[PDB]
Length: 109
Length: 213
Length: 221
Image (cartoon, rainbow over all chains, first blue to last red; front, side):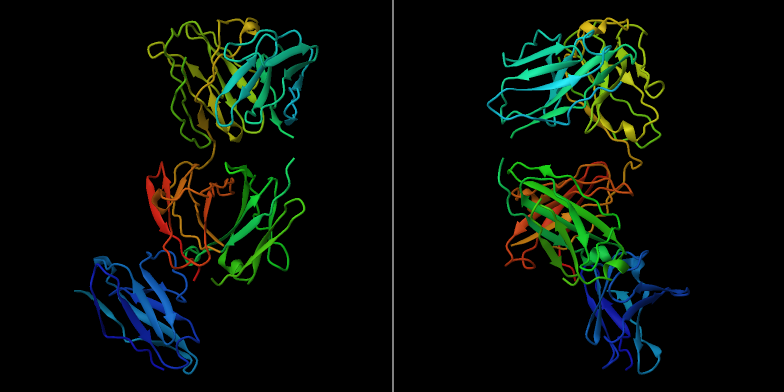
């Protein structure tokens, strides 16, 4: 029931691209999935909560949705100031603890 | 003293009608009475001045007179394609200012009712991602106007800032109206069925939608 | 005669506005220009006359310091400085042409208002100029439309399919919200066989904010 995330992300600027965050059976879908980010050398923040609505204070660039086990993070345009370290947050009832992905590193091609 | 006028004039075409403007002893009689008319969405224009002579630009169609407290403006029938509001003006020495009437709009005198059509538009997800939710429903294809729209959650009506816009006359011989209601996403998702009802003075229909698609 | 002028800019309460209608085709030294406002749903109120030669203007018993006037013989256009704008000031302003000359408070009974034309609009609201942030509205034969909110002042123009569709495009009346916003609704009718297949867009333009948005309408997900 561990979250599966790629160690690196290959995102070309100028066009949209999608990344996946998948778990296992009775791990994604029964509980809501959250998107979290952290600045290098600073405290983390929240990107997308519940994969339904975007919180205030965050620009409308990241689209959050769930498709079964795989959770998709849709983006529109890659900017140089939006290279924050992205992470996947989820809740599982078989562990009584939050399960986090391996962490995807976005690098400009 | 405040000069009074009827809110609207009931005048059928093909036969003469007139309007009255009652005033006071120091306002009417000792001073001349002037009548003004304005086009819908345009500038006004004087009709009768000094109660017995008329301006250049109008045919021998209208007549005005003053008799004591009230003054009468006799109209030779009514044209259906030309309907304008009428004004009454005078002067008062104690007020030391020009006083204008309330305004009389002439109305023709009977058509059968139609079948109204109602639609309800739920908010989109882009509205809900900004921590807000608004609900709007519209009524159209009805004649005449004067309709009232109220919201209903199929268990009890809700009053969280309910307003009713005044009907407006279009060019295709049809009246239209709408109602708006803005809420919070917590209360919006509390009820799984929302609808609004219209009152066509004898006809009432319901437009029920769901907060899913 | 002529009275073409410019539309007055919307003023918040506690401000000053100036309106002036151009005078030409005659000599501006013999007709006293008047001023009057057309309140919606009721009559009109008057404050005094302005002779274009000397300082002999007066005031009514309801307008003492709220209205001030100023003549200008070099341009032959009258000027005014409105003060203490409130909710009762919300009316369109018309300058009333008058015949003859009147300086005393008893010579105007033979005077009649000559010409009315091209008045300016004055609406008093705390709101002044704000840029819209209008978001798409989901639809429900079938009907669809986009509603405009968080903008000021009225009106805005809603055009569908880049102005290629004009049948059924009706601007529904707005209402004064508690926060001061408006809501102009425009709807079009499409067959129920095409609801999420054909792309439908509507254009709403804002004049003082210079914001033109091409918002696509989509069903609620």
